[PDB]
Length: 153
Ligand code: HEM
Image 1 (cartoon, rainbow, N blue to C red):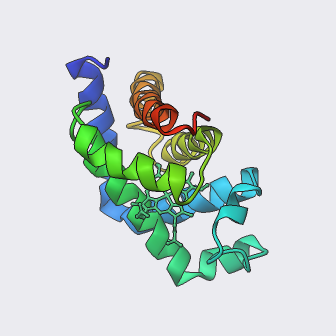
Image 2 (cartoon, helix red, strand yellow):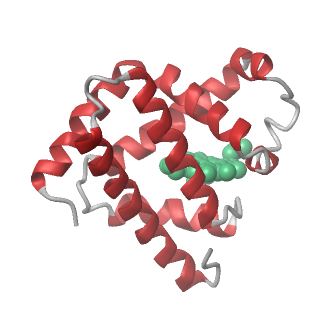
């Protein structure tokens, strides 16, 4: 579990992310798509984007960045009591989109990378450690729903 002190660290940087969800959302997806190109293959709707410049120019891509950060932010603010928000998410991603847990690990790393880039001041080692623990909790809880459904990993 995260301590209260750790959740405050998490939510204080997140409040900065909320100042520009679209910009953060965009960078994180692009970072994910560039680092692990196999992830882009899950999106029929983005499978035509070949360069970073095309990715950066996609308004639909931007809109998906905001969708992802918005749902994640809702989860973070529950500070661990995210059972209701997490369930519908695990179910669609497991059975519908067919996203392996590993890819969740990949987007978590993309999030951490971007935050460090846009908030070097509010994102010190202690905050990076708290953020890591929060995303690990999220993955751990999803993984468990996946396992129940016959999809573990
Ligand atoms: C931080 C973790 C992520 C969050 C919170 C999340 C959030 C969401 C939201 C809310 C939905 C749309 C509603 C729904 O279908 O359930 C969505 C749809 C979907 N997500 Fe994720 N997502 C996450 C990670 C991933 C990753 C890592 C992948 C692929 C690498 C993925 C692929 C998709 C797919 C393919 C759809 C359908 C998009 C479409 O309608 O074309 N998601 N995700």
